[PDB]
Image 1: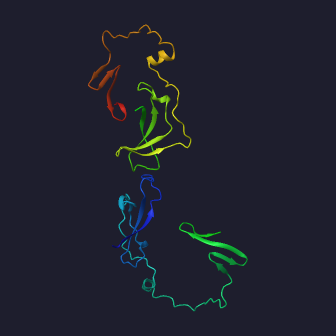
Image 2 (image 1 turned 60 degrees about the vertical axis):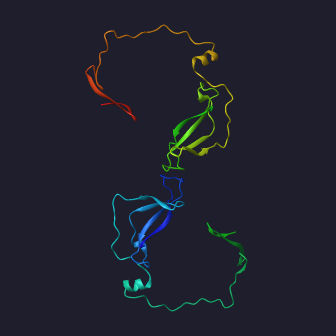
Image 3 (image 1 turned 90 degrees about the vertical axis):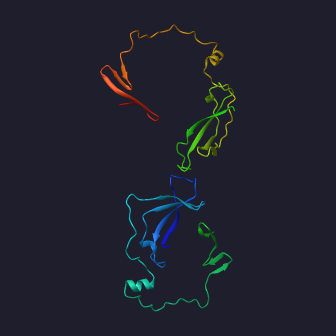
Length: 131
Length: 131
């Protein structure tokens, strides 16, 4: 339950081509759920059949490297306080305010600003699309 | 039943890699079983799953070419007699005879001849293997 993995496309593996929808799992380990797993990668790489939902192969290195026994390299405040004495004091705020509103005008997805006019679109792939 | 094909390895097709044991069929057509099918190839190429014993894909050209309507290009005597008027007359024989036997001596697969001595092996892959 402490073993995690980032699921990636296999990218391309000549052993299977497009004959099977595959993923490769970059394996990591957390000694605690709040850890950043990236300090503890594992040395092998499981290949998974997306549709069949099962591991069909595991790429294992000739040279084996067991889990790192070092502390995880974490970054949340509690972690930091522990790492370095404590967190830096909150800093004086810099507040940004637009009392009379903004100068741009949006009509649906159509934007209007400083003489510019365009449509702001968006899709699953490209993300933002200006037209 | 007039459609034939020479079964080849797919060789290599990046669409499947080694994920499936595949064959590609070079398709031909005989208007008569005694024909040499090679004057009549077809334009498409079926991909077959060896283990599953079934066509999993067919490569079809963008430009279609239907069966040739010409006579098959045959080479057996009956074909030749028809093609050119007739066969050449049998030629005077040249007989080779070794009345007192051969000069080489084989002891099992071991050969001995003209001071040479070697073992004649054979296997499924390489064929003859001299050792």
